[PDB]
Length: 236
Length: 217
Ligand code: NI
Image (tube, rainbow over all chains, first blue to last red; front, side, top):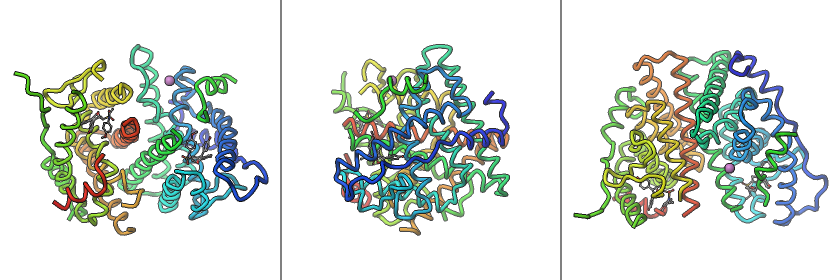
């Protein structure tokens, strides 16, 4: 069904799939320790992951894949998706990151846990970049869907006829989301040149999000969701 | 002048700046020794290649070093994927150093093979390749501060390379829809190259000061 959707049907489907805004654990002890703020962030992320899977299952084309391929897309993309959500939430709070409505953190609280101010600075620069570009909500949901479908696709096996069918399918859906982004920009009134340029600028920011996600795992070096956990939530 | 270049001038300039394909040191008639020595010599060519990317030398030396520091392994890797594209299942590190999976950390070499396979399926063209390599150079470090004038300039050059890619595809006969779809497909592969670079880096060298002396000289 996904490949039959027009651009406006794709946008509406992506807007309606958006997950809820969650709150941080209420009234933690402030100031934080390294241990306590990692604890609040982990608990927030663990609760967001559940709604991430519900969102994923509503991204057109995602459910057509095997459960195994779905779990690998989520394994590769989950932190990037959490991060892009954080960046989108933070756009109108320059210099700060809005993890939840009740957990707004500035740069110098990032210094709390070792290794995290560097990622805070990158997250803040991405939020400024999105503010610079006047990123639109309809563009943001297309980007988040691209992250989900693209980040793990290069890891499909190609061993079998099916694996090529799975990976050709993802690329067809990614093509449709590209078409949808372009359609939104033409409907805004951008010229053809401006459309191609904005498309490239948005997709190039996705390589920075991938970088920050990689950087974050590396400073971390068992809080990442396991295959079995992601599979069980997918089947639930 | 970089902002005044036509699409055909951008491609010409990048094609003319392309480094040669280097050989491994083997003499007959260690794997890392060989790869390190190869990368060592490719980096010397990379620095002088970067100075010829339109708009790059307009930046302060500090910003030039910051971009090279962030992109050097991505650049080596995209060069390897390009070379290996017509050798399915193998990585052509050099014409005399062609390795298969067994000879390989293996994870990165599975990822490199998947990238080469993707470029093969898309019939990636040499003119598109040089464009993508320059995008890696200019884009990988820009969000890490490479101030405001520098960042704007870089974005105007990136917009020119976008125009160049679109022009190439229009001249190859692609429809407007195909042009934007292919642009997106090529740029999404850069996210995977960034990931392979990060992984290789964290499985494990040129410092900030090394790159600046190399680029001073
Ligand atoms: Ni796995």
